[PDB]
Image (cartoon, rainbow, N blue to C red; front, side):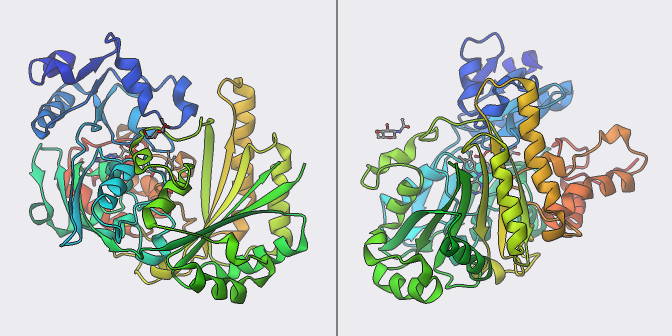
Length: 500
Ligand SMILES: *Cc1cc2c(nc3c(=O)[nH]c(=O)nc-3n2C[C@H](O)[C@H](O)[C@H](O)COP(=O)(O)OP(=O)(O)OC[C@H]2O[C@@H](n3cnc4c(N)ncnc43)[C@H](O)[C@@H]2O)c(*)c1C
Ligand SMILES: *[C@@H]1O[C@H](CO)[C@@H](O)[C@H](O)[C@H]1NC(C)=O
């Protein structure tokens, strides 16, 4: 494999195990610290192209020598699939493929896969205070992965997901052909906008629609005690109102221990605080929030704020490539909720936070509705639309270095929490969020360990219909057309219809 690469691409973009910088390049975007001790995080080579023509030979060498491709842009995949495999593999790391072209007059931008959300937001904000992009929250996330999987954040109720706002793309397929929207066709251009683009090809660049944002947005955040009847009433009404209120207001909810359970309420309102005050006093008067609890800022300042930087920090903090906190290993799972959880079941859920160490486990609510209930189930592969109140996320975290038995304890905790919620969350299929990737919901069999093509597809649909509902089956046909030999494979790759 390595011989084939070195006779075809410059040595300067090739990092093998023997290279002293291999470990830095590997670790630099291993973004879930849980996998820093994974035995499957051992690519034989990391390739870091700096121009497009570097990529086609890596496809050729990968096919000819049986070395599986793992595509990494931001490396934020929550299961670390961009840098692990149980078969011999290499990482095509697109960090240097990162140019951004912003057209303020046409309200559009071309963004290469290795650019981060922070770099995109930075480039927009340097040119206009009133344009934005609803890309998601984390400034270090790569657009290469994010825009292929949905991409949710404080703007999604107002403007849609990141994948709801894509108008062209450049993609390299398994034959090494570099295609745009016109030459890839509408089916494949549909599939990559939220279907997990790495099942179909290597996205080189996305063309996005820029959104009009108000020159003033308003944020607020407060921490309350859960053992407080006003907090409980607010949360009771939150379940019923968060997805139905004014689409300009998005409110997140989080719970952790600190010994009591605290409730974190955080929000962004796409408007001034004079507009926000009557809305909050009509929807949640029990919060008692005054004029001075709302802080006005620009759209990009609100992104800086919610990435744990100072409100008045220079925009350059958006260009940093690692999070502004030291991260703990973690395992998250998520569910979709269509009916309010009963009061006493919510109490039983939150009490499970007492079972592990203080402040290390979390339950979080991300509301749907708004624009997300206006878009059909099949507009793009992302299917989680009207009828969903919120996505409910469960997470356990621990410190780097805990022994195996304690990690298993943490994994078992969050899995049992998930199992306990089966009666109260979506079913048939039990929905799951691709960008909250969870291997526990099902993985592919080894294609050689199936008994038929139908068998391969049906097994894969276990996880497939959870992420995509029946968009999964349209994606199976598209996969069959554009990658019939299954060059792009991994634990949750869309399967082709195998010929024999
Ligand atoms: C670490 C982190 C992740 C976050 C954060 N906040 C999020 C939020 O507010 N909303 C979300 O919806 N997701 C959030 N995430 C998760 C990540 O945004 C998603 O998990 C993305 O999928 C990660 O994208 P990226 O940064 O590129 O990480 P990768 O591992 O490189 O990509 C994930 C996935 O996509 C494939 N892939 C990447 N690049 C390509 C290209 N060019 N072509 C095809 N396929 C590609 C990878 O193989 C992998 O499977 C907040 C934080 C702190
Ligand atoms: C982010 O960029 C700013 C500007 O240089 C810098 O002050 C800050 O330390 C950076 N954040 C990091 C290194 O996490």
